[PDB]
Amino acid sequence: APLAPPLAEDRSYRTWRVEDYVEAWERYHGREMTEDERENLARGCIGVTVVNLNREDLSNPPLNLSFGSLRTAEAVQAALNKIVDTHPSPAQYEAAVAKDPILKRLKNVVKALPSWIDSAKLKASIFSKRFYSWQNPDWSEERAHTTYRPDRETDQVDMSTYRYRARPGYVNFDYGWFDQDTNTWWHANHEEPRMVVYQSTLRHYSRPLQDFDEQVFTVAFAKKD
Ligand SMILES: [Cl-]
């Protein structure tokens, strides 16, 4: 039973009072949201994703495994879920990753595993991040506009230069949590107060905006309930 129903056929998004989202969240995860979790949620869009990763070792969603297209992220998700479904130790995970036709060509796959969480408690999850390319005002325009181009072979986007810099006069980022039960994207407007949670179609979440000129689809390990 999904956290929320799907969107109507003629709807691009549904808006949620934070209080109503939390109740739906608590029904779905079958437990009360903690104070640390509520505090993370109050950070806005980034909080929706941090709370859903369910990982106390994270304050920000990890960008290690970021890709130019949703389909690549979905393939990487399936590959990773297949490996952690065998309950590997960290060393067994590294070996498995090395043999996997998709994962072995990627950067940061080994780093993506949280060693202190047993692999039987993990699942690969997806979120989409929108951001501004000009992360250093000193960069030339050519550098800004090529730094986050996806690898022509693996579709992987190098995020190591990313500094959470906003386009001057705009919001720094958006994060959208991929709800694969209903095929919607969960985000928010900004941090508390007056935070509103959004449940959007991918097209609406991805729509042209002055704030952002880059979008990636990112795979990260979440901790199961
Ligand atoms: Cl739409």
Image: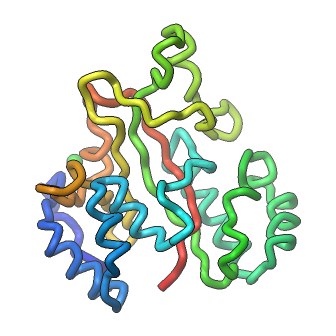
Query: Measuring 20% from the left and 81% from the top, which residue is drawn there?
Result: 23
Query: Measuring 14% from the left and 75% from the top, which residue is drawn there?
Result: 20
* Residue furthest out toward the bottom: 30
At which x and y percent is residue 133?
A: 46, 25
Q: Quarter holding the N terminus?
A: bottom left
**In the figure, is residue 42 to the left or right of 88?**
left
* Up/down of 18 relative to 187, above or below: below
How many numbered badges does the structure rendering display?
0
Q: Nearer the viewer, residue 62 or 58?
A: 58
Query: Measuring 40% from the left and 35% from the top, which residue is drawn there?
Result: 131
At which x and y percent is residue 158?
A: 63, 35
**In the figure, is residue 140 to the left or right of 170?**
right
Query: Measuring 81% from the left and 52% from the top, which residue is drawn there?
Result: 104
* Up/down of 40 relative to 129, above or below: below
At which x and y percent is residue 221?
A: 58, 66
* Up/down of 126 relative to 26, above or below: above
Q: Quadrant of residue 150?
A: top right
**In the figure, is residue 151 to the left or right of 207?**
right
At which x and y percent is residue 94?
A: 83, 64
**In the figure, is residue 161 to the left or right of 210?**
right
| Model colouring | rainbow
